Image (cartoon, rainbow, N blue to C red):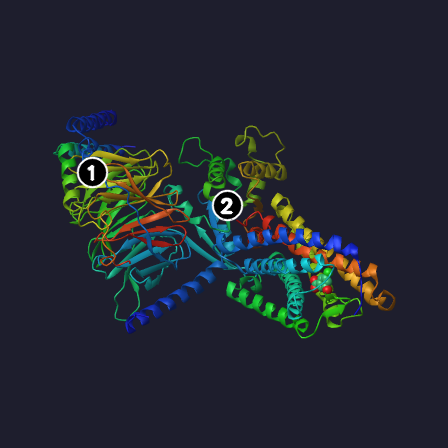
């Protein structure tokens, strides 16, 4: 209607482009977007291995589910200017080393790597863009932490800690201290897993947390959540 | 062809139907408005809930005439063809409402128990193809009501009824029993599986929103059984003792009263499906 | 920590060249912007809407 | 200590610059402009709605033919739009889907984009093969690339989040000129009409005027209280306007080297993502985080109109080179054309 032959053919080309865009969007909607975070090179590599310079794309499939895990390491800038790009991710995978409770960051004087991880977790968890985004917290290097906690007590890291110098109690205390940074407990869930250097069930934990998040999302659609 | 004089019915049916129509038309129309304008993007599930709202609404539109029939001491003076259209409409909208309740239950079962399944990936166009195929199968299985004369004339009192107290109507009684027991089994299975699954996830179960969803999944099943079991039971009791119960006043009154609980379902449907939704605008 | 002296020298050199810049009065610049706005006011389709015959997005 | 002496000298130079700015300011833009007629109420209607993006649209750019568009969204798709007919001329799949900027060449031959991959990718639109392929990928930025602007088919200035602007040679792919001096991450970029100078707004609440052919900062403009996210020259190239997170738009002049007028309202508290000027410069269009674009009287600091109709944050703005239409992009995956 009031179109030339070239106009009609351009409209047909636009409709083909729309079709391919719809197919690409439907392909990308079934993918799981995960934001990988952590304080420096602490346990991100190990995890990436268990699952498989700007942003790093890690692709892996588990139980007929494709995962898109994004590493924002070596993006040394203001986080708030690009952290809204990951507002629609399924979950945040936060990697924390357990063995750096007594190490120093060496960038600031009298700075703890553990407390830097706590501050980064407090900023990420209570961020305005991640109000309803669940966090899969990974506590890296449990065996190294277990064998070094005998030599170095955790009280040098947490002065208010008064428990025994055992792996289980101090690990639970560290997990509780990280979960206490969540001020939005009524609207988001934090999944904590303790991972060794060579631990096979890391993917299954990510799949279970992502499945919970997907169930949450599914309910909203059925107007049931 | 008989002459029942259940004055009782003329005092309980007229009001029940007025209340059901007034509340259900409002609720279903508001739900349809929310679905059609406010909700900007639809997903296969919104297509099923919208079709359930339609069936429920259409059935509330068919109530006004049934009320006149009941106000005139059960005298149908709108003709013969209008009688077959009213009976057809009511039956089809009760069948479609049941079918879309079962569809919604199955969709929730697949969304909760098989989150990563292909059924959940279909598009709203495939959803619109199933809802139209289901509507077509509903209309085909209820057309018999348009191929017979339902008007019984006695003492200048015409009675337009499909559940005849004379004897078993046949397919109407069969369809009446299946349209409950079959979806009943599907809904019970889906509800039990959904709740059970939800519980296993202890991190998710602890949320208040998860507890509310688990409660409403059981609420919807309770309503269906409490609204559709009385009439099915009454009809079964009549069928079994057809000889003695033939044209029985008490059985007729029980059947007519219990048949209004199905209309009550289509009036509470928008309450337990749309207004109870914490996310539907 | 002796490398900060070069950064400080670069900063004060940038500030020194930025200080030695000829500046016209803000009244003159305001009048220049106002004159540019008035000279091109008729050829502004957003400020002065064109008729629908001349509008390509009709 | 030489360091303390140089800090004292820098403080003295800053005080001298501030005193030279204060002594040179006699009558503000309001005091001269309050005696002319206002623009009235500027009402614009959505003429086209460009659908097809499926994620948040982060950037746009208009063609110099005032008809062709390019838009970037987190789909990983650069869609080129025929805005007259609402037709998709091209759809360019991106290697990195985290795109935050896009530019369209003045000749129309090329499209650039960039983002969290720290790479400005040049796309050849008019190829012999009939597809849009990557001309080259410009690498060398150590931070996220926040804005890019074509000078010609071979020159491009790219803003980035490594506190550094950069001028590239697309023939060689090499870092021709590096612009340094910003403290925070540089978030916006705007070329002069003659492409002799350009301004950049960064996260240090500062705007800097650079020269392309000398590669060093001429003037530094301050006054904002938060991160500058948008910047745009006045159409004669002698002034520019910024937009930041403190809900204020400031107008700066290059010759006066001062802030002239603040475009702020009490009812506006959210940040500003995009800032664009009309053809005459009388209207200043700013996209905000409260989901709509506010047209400002650029000479009088009056809200000339509101461009409402986006369900999410308006992230990018663009006025055509003939001034005919303004296009607003937003996080709700839609582009709208206004007249
Ligand atoms: O189809 C119905 O819903 C129906 C039919 C009757 O003949 C009587 C009653 Cl009470 C209901």
Q: As drawn, is A60 to the left or to the right of B238?
A: left
Q: Position of residue A190 (x, y in %)?
A: 56, 44
Rendered view: C12 above or below C51: above
Host chain of mark 1 = D
- Which residue bears the numbered disc 2? A95
Disc 2 versus disc 1: distance between alpha carbons?
61 Å
Numbered disc in front, either 2 or 1: 1
Q: Position of residue D37 (x, y in %)?
A: 20, 38
Rendered view: D161 above or below D2: below
* Residue A206 appears in the picture as rendered: no
Q: Quadrant of ligand 1?
A: bottom right
Please tell me which residue is depicted at 44% across the width and 37% down the height of the picture. Answer: A105
Q: As drawn, is D338 to the left or to the right of A147?
A: left
Residue farthest along the bottom direction in this orientation: B147
Quick one: B204 or B230, which is closer to the camera?
B230
Please tell me which residue is depicted at 78% across the width and 56% down the height of the picture. Answer: B7
- Which residue bears the numbered disc 1? D37
Q: Position of residue B99 (x, y in %)?
A: 65, 64
Quadrant of the rendered image containing residue A143: top right
Does mark 1's beta carbon lie closer than 8 Å to ligand 1? no
Quick one: A224 or A206, which is closer to the camera?
A224
* Residue D28 appears in the picture as rendered: yes
Q: Position of residue D173 (x, y in %)?
A: 24, 57
Quadrant of the rendered image containing residue D33: top left
Residue farthest along the front direction in this orientation: B156
Check if mark 2 and mark 1 are on a common chain: no
Host chain of mark 2 = A
Tag 2 near tag 1, CB within 8 Å:
no
Does mark 2's beta carbon lie closer than 8 Å to ligand 1? no
* Rendered-image quadrant of the N terminus of chain A: bottom left
């Amino acid at each position: 209607c009031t179109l030339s032959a070239e106009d009609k053919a351009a409209v047909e080309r636009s409709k083909m482009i729309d079709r391919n865009l719809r197919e690409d969007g439907e392909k990308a909607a079934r993918e799981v977007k995960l934001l990988l975070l952590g304080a420096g090179e602490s346990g991100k590599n190990t995890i990436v291995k268990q699952m498989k310079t700007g942003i790093v794309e890690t692709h892996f499939t588990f139980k007929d589910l494709h995962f898109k895990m994004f590493d924002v390491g070596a993006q040394r800038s203001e986080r708030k200017k690009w952290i809204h790009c990951f507002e629609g991710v399924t979950a945040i995978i936060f990697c924390v080393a357990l063995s750096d409770y007594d190490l120093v960051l060496a960038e600031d004087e009298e700075m703890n790597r553990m407390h830097a991880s706590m501050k980064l977790f407090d900023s990420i968890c209570n961020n305005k863009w991640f109000t309803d985004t669940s966090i899969i917290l990974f506590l890296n290097k449990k065996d190294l932490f277990e064998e070094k906690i005998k030599k170095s007590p955790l009280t040098i890291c947490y002065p208010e800690y008064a428990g025994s110098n055992t792996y289980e109690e101090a690990a639970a205390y560290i997990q509780c201290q990280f979960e206490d940074l969540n001020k939005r407990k009524d609207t988001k869930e934090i999944y904590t897993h303790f991972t060794c250097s060579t631990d096979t069930k890391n993917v299954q934990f990510v799949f279970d947390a992502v499945t919970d998040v997907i169930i949450k999302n599914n309910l909203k659609d059925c107007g049931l959540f | 062809c008989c002459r029942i004089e259940g004055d009782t019915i003329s005092q309980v049916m007229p009001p029940l139907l007025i209340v059901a129509f007034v509340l259900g038309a409002l609720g279903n129309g508001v739900a349809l408005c929310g679905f059609c304008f406010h909700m900007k993007t639809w997903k296969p599930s919104t297509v099923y809930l919208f079709n359930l709202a339609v069936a429920d609404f259409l059935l509330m539109i068919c109530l006004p005439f049934r009320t006149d029939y009941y106000l005139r001491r059960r005298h149908w003076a709108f003709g013969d063809i209008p009688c077959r259209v009213g009976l057809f409409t009511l039956a089809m909208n009760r069948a479609g409402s049941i079918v879309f309740l079962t569809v919604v239950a199955a969709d929730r079962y697949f969304k909760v128990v098989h989150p990563h399944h292909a059924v959940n990936t279909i598009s709203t166009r495939v959803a619109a193809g199933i809802v139209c195929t289901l509507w077509a199968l509903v209309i085909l299985g209820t057309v018999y009501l348009l191929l017979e004369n339902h008007l019984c004339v006695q003492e200048t009192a015409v009675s337009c009824e499909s559940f005849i107290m004379e004897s078993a109507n046949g397919w109407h009684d069969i369809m009446f029993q299946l349209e409950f027991f079959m979806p009943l089994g599907i809904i019970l299975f889906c509800s039990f599986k959904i709740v059970w699954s939800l519980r296993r996830r202890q991190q998710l179960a602890r949320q208040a929103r998860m507890k509310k969803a688990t409660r409403f999944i059981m609420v919807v099943a309770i309503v269906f059984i409490t609204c559709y079991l009385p009439s099915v039971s009454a009809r079964l009791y009549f069928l079994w003792t057809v000889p003695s119960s033939a044209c029985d006043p008490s059985v007729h009154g029980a059947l007519h009263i219990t048949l209004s609980f199905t209309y009550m379902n289509s009036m509470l449907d928008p309450l337990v499906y749309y207004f109870s939704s914490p996310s539907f605008p | 920590n002796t490398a900060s002296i070069a950064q400080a020298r670069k900063l004060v050199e940038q500030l020194k060249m930025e200080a030695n810049i000829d500046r016209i009065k803000v009244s003159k610049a305001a009048a220049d912007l106002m004159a540019y706005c008035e000279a091109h006011a008729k050829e502004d389709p957003l400020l002065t809407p064109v008729p629908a015959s001349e509008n390509p997005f009709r | 200590s030489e360091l303390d002496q140089l800090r004292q000298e820098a403080e003295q130079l800053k005080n001298q610059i501030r005193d030279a700015r204060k002594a040179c300011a006699d009558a503000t833009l309001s005091q001269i402009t309050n005696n002319i007629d206002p623009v009235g109420r500027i009402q614009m209607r959505t003429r086209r709605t460009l659908r097809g993006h499926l994620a948040k649209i982060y950037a746009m750019h208009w063609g110099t033919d005032s008809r062709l568009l390019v838009s970037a969204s987190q789909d990983g798709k650069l869609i080129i739009w025929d805005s007259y007919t609402t037709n998709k001329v091209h759809a360019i799949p991106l290697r990195s889907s985290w795109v935050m900027t896009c530019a369209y060449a003045p000749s129309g031959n090329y499209v650039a984009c960039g983002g969290l991959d720290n790479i400005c990718s040049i796309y050849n639109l008019k190829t012999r093969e009939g597809n849009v392929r990557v001309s080259r990928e410009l690498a060398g930025h150590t931070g996220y690339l926040s804005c890019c602007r074509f000078l010609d088919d071979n020159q491009i200035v790219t803003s980035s989040g490594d506190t550094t602007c950069a001028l590239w040679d697309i023939e060689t792919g090499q870092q021709t000129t590096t612009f340094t001096g910003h403290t925070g991450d540089v978030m916006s970029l705007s070329l002069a009409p003659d492409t002799r100078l350009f301004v950049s707004g960064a996260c240090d609440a500062s705007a800097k005027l650079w020269d392309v052919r000398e590669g060093m900062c001429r003037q530094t403009f301050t006054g904002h209280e938060s991160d500058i996210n948008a910047i745009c020259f006045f159409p004669n190239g002698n002034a520019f306007a910024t937009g930041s997170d403190d809900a204020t738009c400031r107008l700066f002049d290059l010759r006066a080297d001062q802030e002239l007028m603040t475009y702020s309202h009490d009812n506006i508290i959210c940040g500003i993502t995009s800032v664009s000027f009309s053809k005459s410069g009388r209207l200043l269009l700013a996209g905000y985080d409260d989901f709509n674009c506010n047209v400002w009287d650029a000479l009088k600091a009056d809200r000339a109109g509101v461009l409402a109709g986006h369900d999410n944050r308006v992230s990018c703005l663009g006025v055509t080179d003939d001034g005919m239409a303004v296009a607003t992009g937003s996080w709700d995956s839609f582009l709208k054309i206004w007249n």
